[PDB]
Length: 44
Length: 50
Image (cartoon, rainbow over all chains, first blue to last red; front, side, top):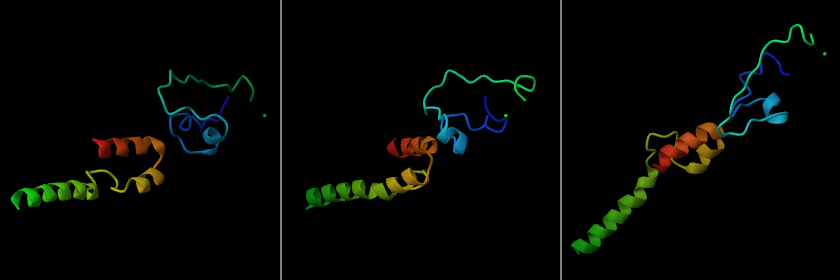
């Protein structure tokens, strides 16, 4: 689970703390990324 | 003299070709390879290589 402003950071070659420190996607073909909202899941 | 001079001139222009930026960001490889992210670095390198 990630911040709403980190969707631009999960990609091949994205600069930022979140990707370059926790999960950096290899700069190659990527199957793909799926996500949705969790306002009723956790919202800590 | 024509053979020697013309061969030398062809080699000279071959070496001179490295100065040209070939529409890339810059000519010297290390500068672009340092001051560009690897994504854009691959594109610029591709341009220079072709």
